[PDB]
Length: 28
Length: 21
Image (cartoon, rainbow over all chains, first blue to last red; front, side, top):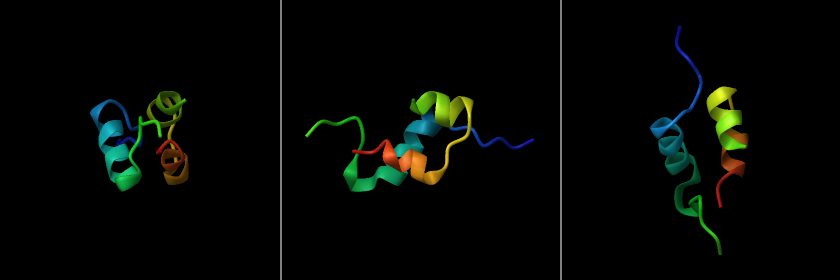
């Protein structure tokens, strides 16, 4: 059945999408 | 962390967003 886990490139893609301009894996 | 919450388990939008800068 369909699954809801975000792994690998899917998790990367999800962070690109939801973080937008805020970004992620950065330091200020 | 994020891999155990989102990949092993399932994460909600606000869990995911809180990992953003």
